[PDB]
Image 1 (cartoon, helix red, strand yellow):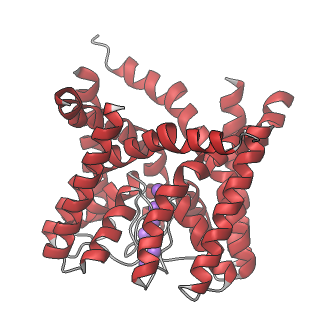
Image 2 (cartoon, helix red, strand yellow):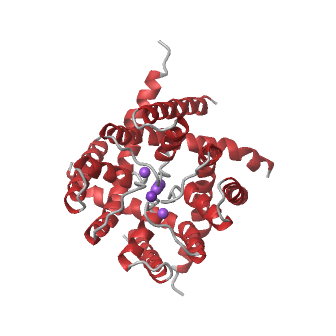
Image 3 (tube, chains in turn yellow, red, purple, blue):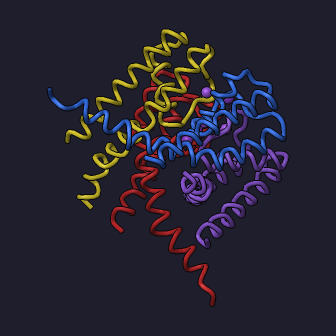
Length: 90
Length: 94
Length: 90
Length: 94
Ligand SMILES: [K+]
Ligand SMILES: [K+]
Ligand SMILES: [K+]
Ligand code: NA
Ligand code: NA
Ligand code: NA
């Protein structure tokens, strides 16, 4: 399904960008930079980190508006695909 | 509603899995592991705890992407099939 | 509009219940108990408090499932009413 | 799209109001006040700061109820009117 495939690609690319940004500008380990990107765009949030640089705060504001809609579109399409085999078996 | 029953069971299994994961790998008490799993997948977040192990961080990323869709599908079906009909019935003057 | 009025009442009643619970079981000032109830059900979250009692953790789990749908229905209906005068003037 | 333009302006005014409020009453630097306003109204939350004054707590409660609806209305219109058409156009082989 192309719509799912394109949403996956867009999501991956968006998360790579955040991982690169937070590891190079905010000094996080790559796994922590990816984690922060994920919990930010899914709106879970993180209780133990917020960006410390003005550049990082501005980036994070724009990153949320650029990425939140795409990530929730991906989460929805992923849910359809993961749940369908159980629905159809049932 | 077969879809509701599926989302209910999958949500329960998802929360059981998180309870087992966070109590085993991150050392949380089971009630705290269940709490963390619920507030993470409903996107509330916990304001104090973050996974400390790299295993926990990777698991949580995958758990979020799969679990948010299931839990909010369940919450939507719960609203449509249970809560809204119950509110409507309870507003009828008798 | 009755649908808005009923959603308002349900939301108020739900927030009062949380305020009573967190102030009596978790020892919060009423304003902090109301604040915690609001940021929990809107999924904002709070970075500086989590329930400390097992009773409070169980309550919070059930409170989220009981209240999240109602609160977002109210937020949506509120948004229609607050935005409409500007839309119609424009 | 007149509705999009209205939601855009109202979102900007809402974020300006929060920036002014949190920098004045809660003592935050303006950039930190804007950051807090954005992560609160998108429901991400900030994992470190909570309003410390009772004024700030009451304001934040009201700001949340009014501002989440505006900001997510804007995000939805931004997705439908700007982001989706741009993605589609950028997928056309030329
Ligand atoms: K915190
Ligand atoms: K959230
Ligand atoms: K959150
Ligand atoms: Na949070
Ligand atoms: Na918390
Ligand atoms: Na944070």
